[PDB]
Image (cartoon, rainbow, N blue to C red):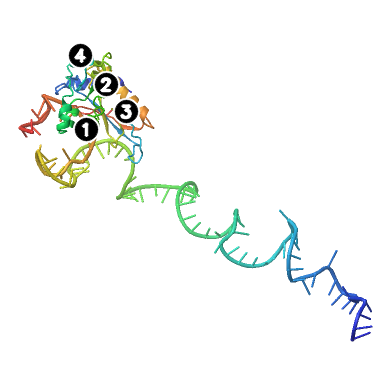
Amino acid sequence: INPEALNKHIAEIIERATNEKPRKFLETVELQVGLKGYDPKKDPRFNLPNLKLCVIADARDADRAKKLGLNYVEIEHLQQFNKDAKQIKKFAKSYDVFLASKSLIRQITVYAGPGFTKAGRTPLPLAPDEDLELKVLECKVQFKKAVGLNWPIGNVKMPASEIAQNIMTTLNFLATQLKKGWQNIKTVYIKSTMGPSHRI
RNA sequence: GGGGCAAGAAGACCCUUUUGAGCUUGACUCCAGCCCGGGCCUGUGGGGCGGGGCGGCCGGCGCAGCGCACAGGGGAGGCCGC
């Protein structure tokens, strides 16, 4: 536990300062969890849920997405989709968040499903009456094949208490998805590109 | 000495009994013996080797782009000059 001392390290990361922050307070510090009993031979790979946000949408939804500064795509790349897939991975990688429209719904389910699914960037279709600008701005756990798991929780520019709440969401997650819970996790370390790690 | 299916003897053969016994073996279940390990008996000093935990450090070769991309990172600044 020790939230004050753990937050003292979160405070130290903000105090060293320096860095190249992108839409976050002191960039993002990701806790690297190590798993004491996890075997690739054993199969528990369940994958479950500012950096870069983006939306593709029509009436009402577009008004509150393009205004938010995310930027929008007019599916003019539908023309590019026939021509090339060279930047398909690149475009999806650039925007951590993709959003969509309920009016569009099946417009590209029949044609532009292609490489965008391999990239995993399936947008969230939002009713024009639905606000949309919240779910996109708000912005991770897969066992996969890697013992080391580091999920960004410093991406919020919100106070270190919210970052600790993101740490608590991360730690609640470690209790929920693991058989020994927090005991199953061998180690955790707070890091950024210029952020030295902090063993939890 | 032909016969009294003459006299000996609750057929020994054969079969039956939920009747035995001796023997056998890779029958069922076991037991002494013996081998082996650890503990106690059981004092007083050395020396090495692992494990566990920390903990630095050195590595990683199917090729376009920059060369063997171990992996999950992060990111327009750290300190590269990149």
Residue carrying label 3: A48
Which numbered disc, 3 or 2, marks the residue that appears first in the sequence?
3
CB under 8 Å between discs 3 and 4:
no
Distance from the alpha carbon under mark 3 to that under mark 4: 30 Å
Distance from the alpha carbon under mark 3 to that under mark 2: 19 Å
Disc 1: host chain: A
Which numbered disc, 3 or 4, marks the residue that appears first in the sequence?
3
Q: In this orientation, does residue A14 appear?
A: yes
Residue carrying label 4: A63
**Quarter the N terminus of chain A occupies:** top left
Residue carrying label 2: A125
Which numbered disc, 4 or 1, marks the residue that appears first in the sequence?
4
Which is nearer the eye, A186 or A138? A138
Disc 4: host chain: A
Residue pictured at 20% horizontal, 14% vertical: A63
Disc 2 residue type?
Pro
Disc 1 residue type?
Gly
On the same chain: label 4 and label 1?
Answer: yes
Distance from the alpha carbon under mark 2 to that under mark 1: 18 Å
Q: Is mark 4 on a helix, strand or loop?
A: helix
